[PDB]
Amino acid sequence: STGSATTTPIDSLDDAYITPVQIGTPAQTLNLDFDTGSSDLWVFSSETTASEVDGQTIYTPSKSTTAKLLSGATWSISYGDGSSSSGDVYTDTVSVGGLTVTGQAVESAKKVSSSFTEDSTIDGLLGLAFSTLNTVSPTQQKTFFDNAKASLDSPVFTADLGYHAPGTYNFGFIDTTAYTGSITYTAVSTKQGFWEWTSTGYAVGSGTFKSTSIDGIADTGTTLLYLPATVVSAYWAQVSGAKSSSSVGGYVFPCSATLPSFTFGVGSARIVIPGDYIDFGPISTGSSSCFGGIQSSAGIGINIFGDVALKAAFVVFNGATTPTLGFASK
């Protein structure tokens, strides 16, 4: 089997991407944030505290003839941005782009933190990291990809995120029309539960490539590119007037600037992030200070190849017995 679904930016900045997902019988379609940095499929629901729902579409398990309470199971998750959610668990039929999994754990939110409530466009998350990170207790549950894998034509999914435009998540096949050149594959460590790999270096604009190992994670659920402070300083030093602002929370730059590209290495191959992809717009409405799309990871503990980086590539998440990542230009 295969599946193919379009993923759409939630706003004009590509702050996140939403993909329609069918849950239950008859189908209830929710727009979920596909997140290769986490491993829970959770949704706003008829069980979510009413004051914490503000415009989201909810899953109502009592209206699904295939929903079953997973008795005794609870979940609770905290994300790197400080947001969180928790609740109980049903199993139900879940379909993405024509690919169906029966008995998928659907984690129903009883509580969500303010940032989720405040984002009316995201009805929940669909985790695509390794199932060892799944938070369901006392019986850990599998991701949608893990459940589907054995049925897929090939044990892979691909992320093709658009810049200020829709893109595609495919399951079970690699669309050879969706990228240019060849796909370069690179090793993955699953030891932390992530799609963790080592970039071979970087360049700023037209500058020379610096060969240096940068361990990080491919994370569709993180907006920006978070890299070591040395790398990030070298980038922003090429932008007149750019500075790190403690009060804003990162590097800012004059909105009048034209940003240089940023290149990252994948083995001997190179992925070029155009400068425009690094512009996240005014820090507050009407400001002439703009927020940068490349930020320091120094306070995180891990480097994160988030959407800014991934949207410049066609990315293969290869879930073969030994997982690997592939990157192609597009």
Image (tube, helix red, strand yellow):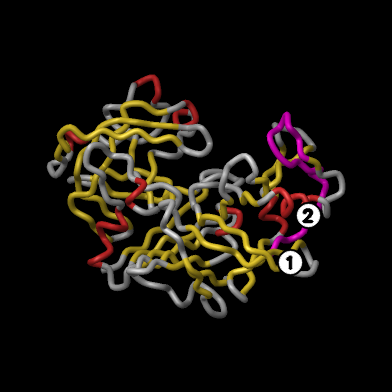
Out of 294 and 228, give the one closest to the viewer.
Answer: 228
Residue 102 placement (x, y as % from top left): 18, 53
Pointer 2 local density, CA inside 10 Å: few below 14, some 14–19, many at least 20: few
Q: Residue at x 45, y 49 (%)?
A: 37
Residue 170 placement (x, y as % from top left): 39, 64
Give the total of numbered labels: 2
**Quadrant in the picture for the C terminus:** bottom right
Q: Residue at x 51, y 57 (%)?
A: 218
- Magenta stretch: includes residue 257: yes
Whether residues under marks 2 and 1 lie with C-beta atoms below 8 angstroms apart, the answer is yes
Mark 2 to mark 1 CA distance (whole Å) = 11 Å
Does 243 sit left or right of 122 as displayed? Answer: right
Q: Residue at x 36, y 63 (%)?
A: 4
Does 192 sit left or right of 154 as displayed? Answer: right
Amino acid at the residue labelled 2: Ala
Q: Which mark is residue 304?
A: none
Q: What's drawn in magenta, residue-wise?
A: 244-263
Amino acid at the residue labelled 1: Lys
Residue 208 placement (x, y as % from top left): 79, 69
- Magenta stretch: includes residue 304: no
- Secondary structure beneath label 1: strand
> Which residue bears the numbered disc 2?
234
- Secondary structure beneath label 2: helix
> Which residue bears the numbered disc 1?
210
Q: Is residue 200 above or below residue 34?
A: below
Out of 6 and 225, give the one closest to the viewer.
Answer: 225
